[PDB]
Amino acid sequence: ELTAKKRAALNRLKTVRGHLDGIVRMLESDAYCVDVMKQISAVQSSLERANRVMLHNHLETCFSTAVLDGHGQAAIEELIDAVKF
Amino acid sequence: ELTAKKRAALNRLKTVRGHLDGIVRMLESDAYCVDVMKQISAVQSSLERANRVMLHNHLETCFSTAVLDGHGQAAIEELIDAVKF
Ligand SMILES: [Cu+]
Ligand SMILES: [Cu+]
């Protein structure tokens, strides 16, 4: 069943797929380079926001409750690739 | 009519919209946070590549042929917002 944050991330993502459609569309109509470039940047910024809600969800959620057991090093170590790999 | 670079940017973008679908889908199935986070990052990296092909197209294209006339300052000045605004 679906979190606070995971819902919003999801809706954010849905919103971004439509944003993407628009860009695909204008590129298809041989749109002005700079305009396309700025849409693409708008999309990336929304992606950044969604990813950080994710992280945030993850930390209080799966991350924390690597309280009990092997948690610790493994949760961290793999958390690290998802920041940049 | 459609450029070298603008074609590829377009196909890249089309590819990314499908990538996005997948993410929307897994989030809908309450997917593992980290996995989702890493897809989202994969999408952003492809966006970065597409944007730079754009830039590259723009520079040889509309940017350059602000050779003649008021070109110069205006093309540059507005080019600058599309790097970060
Ligand atoms: Cu998680
Ligand atoms: Cu251009």
Image: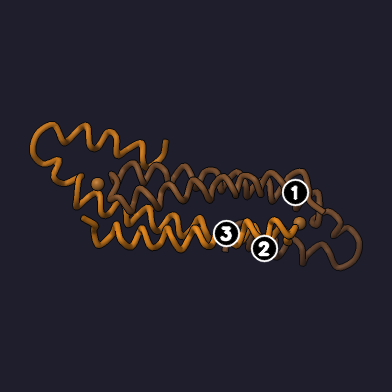
Chain colours: A brown, B orange
Beta carbon at label 1 within 8 Å of ligand 1: yes
Pointer 2 residue: B35
Q: Horizontally, is B54 left or right of A71 in the view?
A: left
Quarter occupied by the C terminus of chain A: bottom right
Pointer 1 residue: A57
* Inter-mark Cα distance, 1 to 3: 21 Å
- Chain bearing tag 2 is B
Residue A56, position as x, y percentages in the image: 72, 47
Q: Would you call the spot at circle 1 few (<14 residues within 10 Å), some (14-19), or many (20 or more)?
A: some
Of the numbered discs in the image, which one, if any, rests on residue B21? 3
Secondary element under disc 1, as helix, strand or loop, is helix
Q: Horizontally, is A9 left or right of B84 in the view?
A: right
Residue type pointed to by label 3:
Asp
Q: In which quarter of the view is residue B77 placed?
A: top left
- Chain bearing tag 3 is B
The residue nearer to you, when weighing A39 against B1, is B1
- Whether marks 1 and 3 lie on the same chain: no
Secondary element under disc 3, as helix, strand or loop, is helix
Q: Horizontally, is A39 left or right of B80 in the view?
A: right
Disc 2 or 3, which lies upstream in sequence?
Answer: 3
Residue A75, position as x, y percentages in the image: 76, 63
Secondary element under disc 2, as helix, strand or loop, is helix
Residue A53, position as x, y percentages in the image: 68, 45
